[PDB]
Image (cartoon, rainbow, N blue to C red; front, side, top):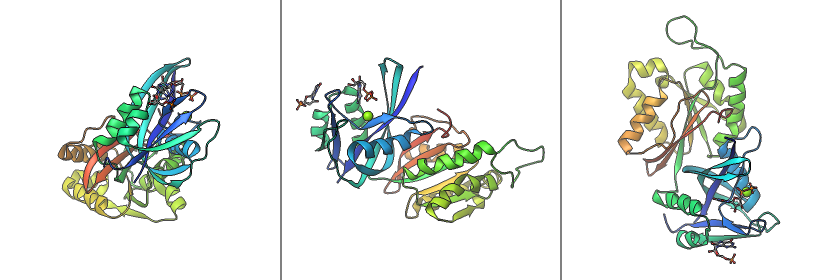
Amino acid sequence: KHTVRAAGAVLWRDPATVEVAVIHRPRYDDWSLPKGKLDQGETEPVAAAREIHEETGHTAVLGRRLGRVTYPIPQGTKRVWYWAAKSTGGDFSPNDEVDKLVWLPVDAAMDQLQYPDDRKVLRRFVKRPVDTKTVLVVRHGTAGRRSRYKGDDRKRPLDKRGRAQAEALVAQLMAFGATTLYAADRVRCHQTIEPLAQELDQLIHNEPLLTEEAYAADHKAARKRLLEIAGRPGNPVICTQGKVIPGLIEWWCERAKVRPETTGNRKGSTWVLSLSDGELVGADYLSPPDEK
Ligand SMILES: Nc1nc2c([nH]c(=O)n2[C@@H]2O[C@H](COP(=O)(O)OP(=O)(O)O)[C@@H](O)[C@H]2O)c(=O)[nH]1
Ligand SMILES: Nc1nc2c([nH]c(=O)n2[C@@H]2O[C@H](COP(=O)(O)O)[C@@H](O)[C@H]2O)c(=O)[nH]1
Ligand SMILES: [Mg+2]
């Protein structure tokens, strides 16, 4: 430490036929990618989306994560996680902070980008498909402690913290354009995604096949259910339990030969599974919204 947390993006619009946005900032006279520090209570994806909008005028849908860049600054170390971000429209107007934005194909953007780490990010971007759909696998938020009773406490609810995580997850799941909601047949799973359900005004599909008991009883039915959900149109959120997620994630990653750059399994965490034509092309583990 001290680590100053930030996030940014390769903002793109219509493989390597797309155009990407490169910005110019007067204060530093640099050509780079949009990025900015996280505000109080923001996560990286929420900050990336916000900074794309504030600097370029565009709204966007985040997809694949593109790695991390660190460099020293007087306060310590700046850390920047980057996402591919598909433009959903907007218009750039110059300001004091960013006076120019150019939309360039990857090759010319490579030439325009002055920092080696930005070119490294853009190399990662072109490495895989960027027109992806997304499956968000979420482990439910904190819900106190398991009781002494055998098995699972079906009705045990989120605790105060878990409720806050559920609220903070709305903005992070919307940053990836979540559209449809699923939770394992436990109260704490449904409660984690209820604030998002309110915000989209949508129903949560119940998933008894994805509880810990059912995964332990019939792991192949769970796996098959996950792929059925993934196959539906739209970007599903699936909220389940700690003994389920690692095994489903490691199975999908191993069969699609996809390497996660980070890994964890914390309550309130999210896995961002990027799909192109049904093949897994990214698996990005995001910390709980109130952890680093
Ligand atoms: N945007 C960007 N700036 C970088 C990088 N590396 C790097 O050393 N810098 C420099 O870091 C300094 C601080 O820039 P930064 O954008 O991190 O600061 P701020 O959040 O705008 O205050 C500037 O002089 C940049 O030229 C980089 O990869 N991207
Ligand atoms: N504006 C600017 N451009 C720089 C710098 N360094 C640096 O390598 N370049 C590159 O110089 C080219 C553009 O110069 P201008 O048109 O003068 O902004 C781009 O290739 C940038 O990547 C720099 O500090 N300022
Ligand atoms: Mg910035």
